View 1: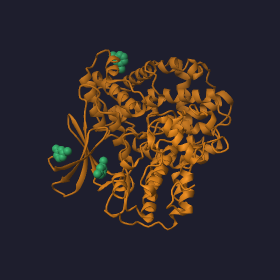
View 2 (view 1 turned 45 degrees about the vertical axis):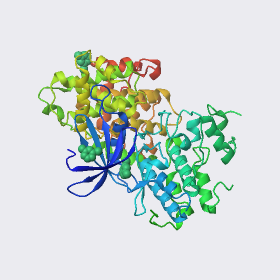
View 3 (view 1 turned 90 degrees about the horizontal axis):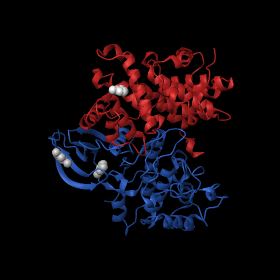
View 4 (view 1 turned 30 degrees about the horizontal axis):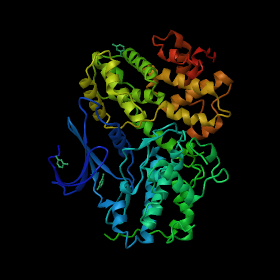
Length: 287
Length: 259
Ligand SMILES: Nc1cc(Br)ccn1
Ligand SMILES: Nc1cc(Br)ccn1
Ligand SMILES: Nc1cc(Br)ccn1
């Protein structure tokens, strides 16, 4: 079954177990393999994998990681993925002193949005967008990955799992524990990610839910009904040069992504027009 | 607002329509099953309705389950004594897909009265996944309904309830309802309910969205008008039972129109 794959090295661990880089002995294709242990006497195939696999089989966009195969055994499941050099977080870290050029930022954000818009157009929420889950190659691409915390939504949305999105990237309507959330939460995350590519530090690095709330308020302005109609009624509500290097258009897009009100928060579709991406190119990254 | 994904509501509808064809069961599958029948499938679906109420599952979970079953029996000969094993495994799969807090496997074994072992359930799980090639994201009657509800004005509790009742009654009878697409059944269920509680038809705004007229929806509306009329005489009662409760505003207690 995996007779044709040769293990090269471990590249990370996720919900499931271990992700490895491997090579197809017969084709030379370098791949990433995700080993998922099956609970054959207890809880069977994890729902994480049921969602990841079923949703990735539908999404075939140049900015969504490609699942090339699913190799079954009695006891193990291997997901075969296309290999991407690294994740945005490692790249950011590599670039903390040099910086990431503005053209490449622009390109990465453009792609991320094209990817994400495809998700939304196909009733899928990602719900875990953070730099560690975004993969880049050496030819200047970026792609959404790790769709284990993803959900196929209905219209209108109903109540989904609340424990969603790493704290730092978690939108205010999840924090405050609102009953319903939707495609807006992914945009928030991307907005947090835009900011991070520009500064190479995270925008809202909280130690707790309460700290996270305070971190947002002080930056975007204590939300009020005039800015976020409803903020005061939200279940857990209670009594600039954010990015120096960034142009006038940049700052406009960012605010629209980081809007408090999920209804007023820009869609991925809208954002793909924002003047910021009028001169977008596809630079190669320095790595 | 954003909970109705305004900038995507259309692309999503179009996608679901394209996908409801790909996830469509074989209309003739039961005549090619040497050992099982439409009637046995009736018992199976009826039993799944009951399980969804004891475990308080989403109705959407029930629809997926039935999709999983029809696609599985569209590809695999199954003997009667295993028909329940397939259905239990589908419900389990639909729960893992759709529910925030799915029942554990042990509860899926408990409901079969230990007709089957845990190993069998879990093995059948894997087989169902392989046969469906992990395509679990099937559009359902409900996914069309919840969209079709947003074209009411005002919103109506009883019409929404009543539409779901009819939708679920369709899941029980392969004949005729396998030869209709979910989007269609959904539309036929919406009209019938609107009329019954208000006197109003399939609205115009939905005709523009779907390309479906009352004329094109007549066959299904007929079959379904019958089902509603014969509902108290149907050998399977679990849905009626279920919709006689406040949660669904006893829409099962309502007398259907005449024509
Ligand atoms: N059997 C295997 C497993 C991995 Br991981 C890589 C190659 N072969
Ligand atoms: N390096 C990687 C990891 C995954 Br998961 C997918 C693609 N490339
Ligand atoms: N033995 C059985 C099988 C089903 Br399906 C429902 C009830 N009892």
